[PDB]
Image: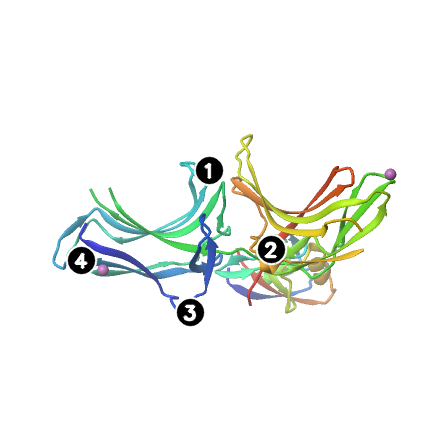
Amino acid sequence: GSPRVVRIVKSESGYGFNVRGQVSEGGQLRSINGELYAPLQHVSAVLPGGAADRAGVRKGDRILEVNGVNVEGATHKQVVDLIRAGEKELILTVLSV
Amino acid sequence: GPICEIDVALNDGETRKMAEMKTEDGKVEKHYLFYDGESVSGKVNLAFKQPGKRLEHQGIRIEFVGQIELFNDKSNTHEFVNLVKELALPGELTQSRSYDFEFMQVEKPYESYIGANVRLRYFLKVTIVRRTDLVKEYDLIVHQLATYPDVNNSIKMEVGIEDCLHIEFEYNKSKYHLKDVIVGKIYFLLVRIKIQHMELQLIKKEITGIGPSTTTETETIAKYEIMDGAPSIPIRLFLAGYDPTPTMRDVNKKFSVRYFLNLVLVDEEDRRYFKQQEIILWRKAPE
Ligand SMILES: [Hg+2]
Ligand SMILES: [Hg+2]
């Protein structure tokens, strides 16, 4: 689950992925790949053949950054709103399962 | 046996940081400090008292163990974490030998807790399998870090009879970090009746039960003696002088540790008034 970048070019309607995770800000620091992170949102769904699927976003991926902006500890609304900037290219930094 | 002693030496050695946990006696014990996900690697050194002396053993092992030990008597003990590294197969040793070990990314979910009715421990255990095996334990400490925003929740608790006496205590957050300052004010909204004594106390509740079986041990971390009595007042409680642990909740269902603010008041009638609220403690990363 080492961190990698993913560039999703808005296709048609969506980025073609969904995010689920905590409602609260902050939380415990837990290891992913021996590295400590505050709680992270993750990719709950990927639409097959959608824009995120072609970009190589996988189910379960935990989002460390959105367009280079670290989102450790963020609430679900914060991240979701940040994805919905509406910008035609979205870049995620993700920690795979 | 023929071994003078079993030595465990971490690679991190001088550089790695250490932490102090209170033993049951209250002496300080110093050990190397680890976090979740960190590797545990080093060398196991076995020294013979006399060289050329055959020892026949069934095996040589080192383990990494996270243990929960409940009520001080055995054996509700279970190991939530167990890694094994075999250093040597059944055979023999005729001369001092120095094994390498490496546990690569080690789950350490829970912070070490030494309690009156419960103990959560991490250790390296070297075992030499014989005939009664020889065992050596090397103690490790784990801290649980967290992060929370600097905001003011501005909670309050009140001690109130009704129209004749009313006392309010207001403090800035419900979640404090281990070196934080609790910031408060005690408002005398109403005093139709003289106050003989007032106390603010920070206490810890260790709850060490399984299912219906349940037990609480309570200890008083601090006392704020607001009134010897009797005539608002700013409250600052400095957590850093004390030695609290983070809130630990339902750890493996075996136990919980929680921290409460208590407002205690005694009136002219020697009637006691009591209000209690829970606050959450966390450990802020060093860096
Ligand atoms: Hg020796
Ligand atoms: Hg009265």
- Nearest to N terminus: mark 2 or mark 4: 4
Q: Secondary structure at mark 1?
A: loop
Viewer-nearest of labels 1 and 3? Answer: 1
Residue A53, visible in the rendered structure: no
User: Under 8 Å from ligand 1: the CB of mark 1?
Assistant: no
Rendered view: B249 above or below B239: above
**Residue A17 horizontal/vertical position (percent):** 65, 56
What is the spatial separation of the Cα atoms under label 2 and label 1, in whole angstroms? 25 Å
User: Badge 2 local density, few (<14 within 10 Å), some, or many (20+)?
Assistant: many
Amino acid type, label 3: Thr
Q: Chain of mark 2?
A: B
Residue B49 has which mark?
A: 4
Q: Nearer the viewer, residue B87 or A62?
A: B87
- Nearest to N terminus: mark 1 or mark 3: 3
Residue B47 sits in quarter: bottom left
Amino acid type, label 1: Phe
Q: Chain of mark 1?
A: B
Please tell me which residue is depicted at 39% across the width and 52% down the height of the picture: B123
- Nearest to N terminus: mark 3 or mark 2: 3
What is the spatial separation of the Cα atoms under label 3 and label 4, in whole angstroms? 31 Å
Query: Pointer 3: what residue?
Result: B15
Query: Pointer 1: what residue?
Result: B71
What is the spatial separation of the Cα atoms under label 1 and label 3, in whole angstroms? 36 Å
What is the spatial separation of the Cα atoms under label 4 and label 1, in whole angstroms? 39 Å
Rendered view: A58 above or below B78: below
Query: Pointer 2: what residue?
Result: B282
Please tell me which residue is depicted at 51% across the width and 52% down the height of the picture: B111
User: Under 8 Å from ligand 1: the CB of mark 4?
Assistant: yes
